[PDB]
Image (tube, rainbow, N blue to C red):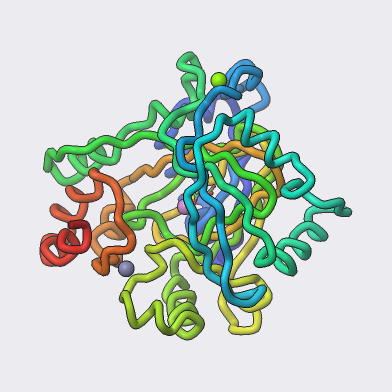
């Protein structure tokens, strides 16, 4: 078995190897990458996502989210308070302000220490989940707006034709902006490209050990667990590396820098934080190996997780028993 300790792997494809996205994913899995839940892909030196970022300041963040924490430093939830719209130029200036800017630090480890010590005492503003793309249309390789769609994959593997679409999303971050512990909708893959700015630190639990993280989460967030049998779908819970180590949960960490891709694999729980002002683009995708994960994915039916139009078909086809109850949740 390849990668039996479930380490995060880093790949350096050549420009030739960068042509065929599907083929490269399948290669990385042949080497065991999926066992970690997360891989890094460094693009060939010849590749670029677009020519410059000089002209992005006029993108609108219609609903910036202030991430307000509750709990203790290593075990907390966050709620998202909606804020007034602002442009990316306005958001960048706010990220760089004395109130929100990255503190002085020695290196990424020192910054990580400071994040976990102090995150809860601040409420950073995240421009998350903005439909759009920063890839140039002429970028032909690993252009996250030109991937094969999940609906097309389902149709190719299973024969069934379904409604829905699959488009990318932009994330504008600042220091301490946080993504809570989650897997993707329907335990899909994700791919995330850091277009510019400061790094993003990731934590990940191997898919084969995801239920260990779930059981800890039920212990640590006991009211939320009684409320919903899949409350990590709400994407609000944080648990620090220190707490994971104290409870014996297997995990790994890695820091993504500008110009690098990350892939999350089916049922790979992940969480993390931004180091400073940045912009990432991410989209969900599928392969043949996902189908079985999709059929087994948990679902929130309490009503909190509220998701996309296109998830309806995935539930309807892959999980027809759960469909009725899940749809009651979504209405
Ligand atoms: O970058 C973020 O805030 C969150 N991204 C992801 O969870 C992802 O790409 O799967
Ligand atoms: Mg602009
Ligand atoms: Ni994710
Ligand atoms: Zn729920």
Query: Which quarter shows the C terminus?
Result: bottom left
Residue 194 figure quarter: top right
Residue 49 in view (yes/no):
yes
Which residue sits at x=33%, y=52%?
289
Placement of 192 over or under 136, stated as above or below: below
Left or right: 126, with 62 as reference point: right
Residue 160 appears at what percent x and percent y? 12, 42
What residue is drawn where x is 39% and y is 55%?
184
Q: Nearer the viewer, residue 107 or 118?
A: 118
Please name the residue shown 67% across and 60% down the image.
122
Is the residue 27 above or below the residue 122 in the image? above
Q: Position of residue 14 (x, y in %)?
A: 60, 29
Q: Position of residue 322 (x, y in %)?
A: 16, 65
Q: Residue at x 49, y 29 (%)?
A: 142
Q: Is residue 55 above or below residue 8?
A: above
The reply to whether residue 1 is in sight is no
Dividing the picture into quadrants, the one containing residue 215 is bottom left
**Residue 140: image location, x then y, percent:** 47, 20
Question: Who is closer to the viewer here, 287 or 94?
Answer: 94
């Amino acid at each position: 078995a390849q990668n039996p300790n479930c380490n995060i792997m880093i790949f350096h494809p050549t420009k030739e190897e960068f042509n065929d996205f599907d083929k490269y994913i399948a290669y990385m899995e042949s080497q065991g990458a999926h066992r970690a839940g997360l891989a890094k892909i460094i693009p060939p030196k010849e590749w670029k996502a677009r020519e410059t970022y000089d002209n992005i300041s006029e993108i609108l963040i219609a609903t910036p989210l202030q991430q307000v924490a509750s709990g203790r430093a290593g075990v907390f939830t966050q709620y998202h308070k909606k804020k007034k719209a602002m442009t990316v130029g306005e958001y960048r200036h706010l990220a760089n302000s004395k109130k929100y800017q990255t503190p002085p630090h020695q290196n990424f480890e020192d910054l990580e220490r400071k994040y976990w010590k102090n995150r809860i005492y601040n409420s950073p503003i995240y421009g998350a989940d903005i439909s759009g793309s920063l890839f140039d249309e002429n970028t032909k390789q690993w252009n996250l707006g030109h991937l094969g769609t999940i609906q097309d994959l389902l149709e190719k593997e299973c024969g069934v034709v379904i409604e829905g679409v699959n488009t990318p999303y932009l994330y504008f971050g600042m220091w301490k902006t946080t993504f809570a512990w989650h897997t993707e909708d329907m335990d899909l893959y994700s791919i995330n490209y850091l277009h510019l700015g400061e790094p993003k630190t990731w934590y990940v639990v191997p898919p084969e050990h995801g239920q260990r993280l779930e059981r800890l989460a039920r212990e640590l967030f006991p009211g939320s667990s009684r409320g919903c049998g899949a409350f990590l779908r709400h994407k609000v819970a944080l648990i620090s590396p220190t707490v994971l180590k104290e409870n014996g949960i297997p995990f790994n960490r890695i820091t993504q820098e500008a110009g690098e891709f990350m892939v999350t694999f089916p049922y790979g729980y992940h969480a993390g934080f931004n180091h400073g002002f940045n912009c990432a683009e991410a989209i969900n995708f599928a392969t043949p190996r996902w189908i079985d994960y999709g059929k087994m994915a948990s679902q929130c039916s309490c009503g909190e997780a509220r998701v996309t139009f296109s998830m309806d078909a995935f539930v309807r086809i892959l999980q027809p028993e759960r469909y009725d109850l899940w749809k009651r949740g979504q209405d």
